[PDB]
Every structure is written in C-alpha cells, then in structure tokens.
Amino acid sequence: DLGKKLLEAARAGQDDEVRILMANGADVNAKDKDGYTPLHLAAREGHLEIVEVLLKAGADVNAQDKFGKTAFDISIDNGNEDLAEILQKAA
Image 1: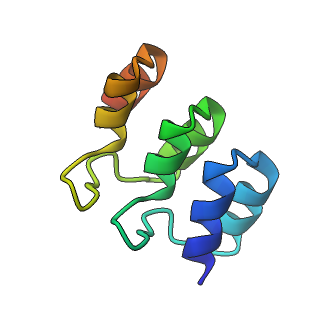
Image 2: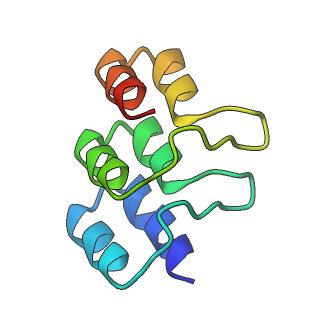
C-alpha cells in the first residue's frame, strides 16, 4: 500500500520520498483509518511545499475526515493563512 507510505512521507514533510512514492503510483487521495489524507496531514503539519506538490498531482482539497473536516478547515483553525489561501485557490 503506497497510499499509507505517502500519508507517512507527507506528514513528515519529506519532499524526496513523497515524489518517489507518487512516481511509483501512490494514490494521492489515499485515506487512513480516520479519513485523513496526505494533503490533510501535510497541511496540518504546515508543510507548504509538500501541499503544493500534492495539489499539482490532483489531491482532493475537499476530502473530509470522519469529522467532516478538510485540509482547509484545519489550516484556518490553526491560523495558517498562507496555507488556507493556497488551498482555497486549488479548490
């Protein structure tokens, strides 16, 4: 499951591993147990570069976790306006 590895690389903000995983066909819209995505995790951890890479590869900005929340919602709640705008523009 390249999806789970991509969730792991994204959260850690590892640009190299993230891109290798995507090139090997990792599902950019993979979800974990609680409905979290690589976009969601990178976004929450404030890895802006990773977010852009994921966005450019078709990451779904509107994907919700089990609580109905998106990458955009956690950016706002965290007060990370740079990220929130980036997400808004890709939606």
